Image 1 (spheres, rainbow, N blue to C red):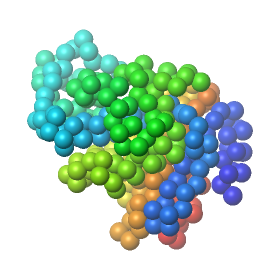
Image 2: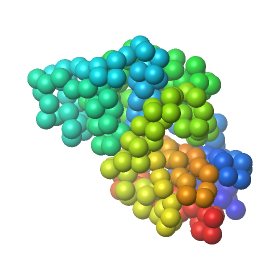
Image 3: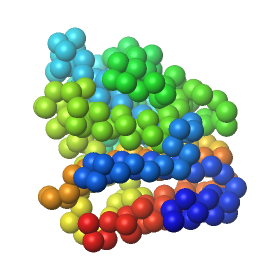
Length: 263
């Protein structure tokens, strides 16, 4: 039993763990604290990029829209954008950097072009997510203060929203294909679910880390002959180091994925 295992793991950490799974092959859903709030951290980047793509689909934002990177605007962890001061970059390229490398300046550029955190929240409400909310830019959104509702989601809401983005009509076919490729090409989450993913499985994911010992991941996994499984794993309010948080996400991923060894 997964519930008992996660409650024991949670007791060791002295924090809160939230998990949600929706298997679209079996139509089975399961969660642990699935409707509780956890910080988004960098897992918001998928949602900012989906908002941007939906604006491109609707004719409200040019596919080739650009914006200028100014040195004074570059924030922490911007491995791609920190080479571009003085240059114009496509907003689409900023989303590629946010999704592949978790580039924070790139994510802020996308947020500034689409109407900010308020616009991402409005997009989420328009596609049926009543829980998730984005309120601040990077890096302030990593605060993850217990009880603070700013920049939060729930494990169930991320699973439901990712399924809406990938399988419903929130995005055009071109846009959902692009978002999926960016999530498959994620380069910064190898120590998490990817480290324990069984052979034959494909993965599209996005992770995050925050203050108060927070870590999280939103993923979609599938096989040639296995319909997508949507998973959320969030941890908060711990004293764990980043390395121990990575190990904990891989540990929870292993417990979920062991069910799929013969799937």
